[PDB]
Amino acid sequence: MIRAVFFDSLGTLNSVEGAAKSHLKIMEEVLGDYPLNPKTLLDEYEKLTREAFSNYAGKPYRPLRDILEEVMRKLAEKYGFKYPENFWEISLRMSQRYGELYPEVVEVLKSLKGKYHVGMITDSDTEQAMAFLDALGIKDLFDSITTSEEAGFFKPHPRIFELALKKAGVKGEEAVYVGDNPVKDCGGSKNLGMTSILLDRKGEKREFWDKCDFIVSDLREVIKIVDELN
Ligand SMILES: *CC(=O)c1ccccc1
Image (cartoon, rainbow, N blue to C red; front, side):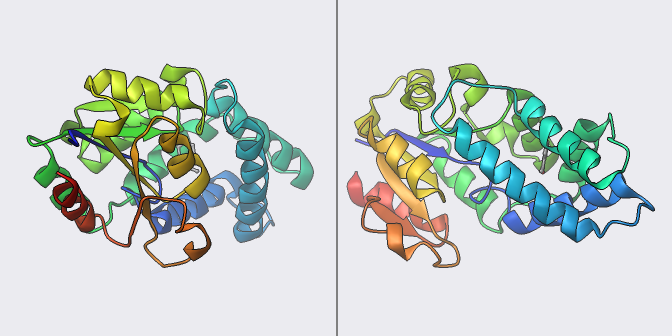
């Protein structure tokens, strides 16, 4: 019996498009009048951050603020502009003003809460996860918010999932996890017997469909699956 439904953050609740728009305005405010194409700075920022997150996958937690400030200090020295000491604050402000939820998030979160435990499991520092849920107005729709900072390990380490299930007081077999990253999400949640639901909004992850238990393009399909199984 499924009694809990857990969600990832980026790509599941808040749109990658909104994050890309926010990230661009972040690099813009960092550069100001500096003669560096903010688009080139962003592409290089995403390349370095992808490499960093890959090195830390499944490993002990390190503050994301430190990891990202390290990347931007390297980019500042590379291109010659002043490292903004308030980079973290700028990222928070812009993320909150231009971040947006997918059109069906609130509807889905409401239909689930009350019937099942509704939780989030995210690779991010707890401060930023809470501030972003608040800026998007959906913090009160979750019964639990579980972060790599709390568990001490990044996904797909099982501890972050273990902690989520413990907060809800359910077994893995009684829980669903929804996300768009086949390895960190389906693989990490499958270790505990959770039902994995892959979210492929644009149908770009067909090569990983055969490993996750279910695949959906819209979160409104999650409620259907939970009913089919119960
Ligand atoms: C990249 C991005 O959106 C971000 C980075 C650090 C803190 C908050 C948001």
